[PDB]
Image (cartoon, rainbow, N blue to C red; front, side, top):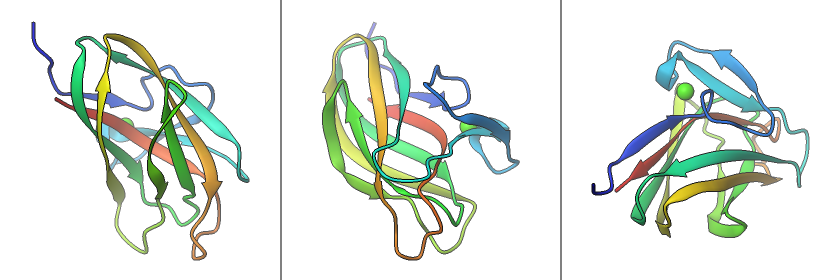
Length: 134
Ligand SMILES: [Ca+2]
């Protein structure tokens, strides 16, 4: 048994809050929107890792005009610079969060709103999926 790449749908994962919504352009046809209205609000996801090792981290979100800017932490550790999820067009936003080493077990992926693009109308996180690339 070696590490396999996996896609974990935000609407299927256990999360601390967030509303499940349908969208024909979302992975799985659904997403989970965290309706943050300002900074320091956070949503937690429980993310299983069956095999210890190194992974590249990819986030898929919806492209909405009120997407915020988020700091990912894993198990309380900052991962990556804050990721600004505002784009001017498109159906989805896909972002590369770099590499980590993850132990075997279930990890806490915390998304904290830390700001928003000046063009954005809000602070929200319409997360579609988390993809762990071995
Ligand atoms: Ca999805």
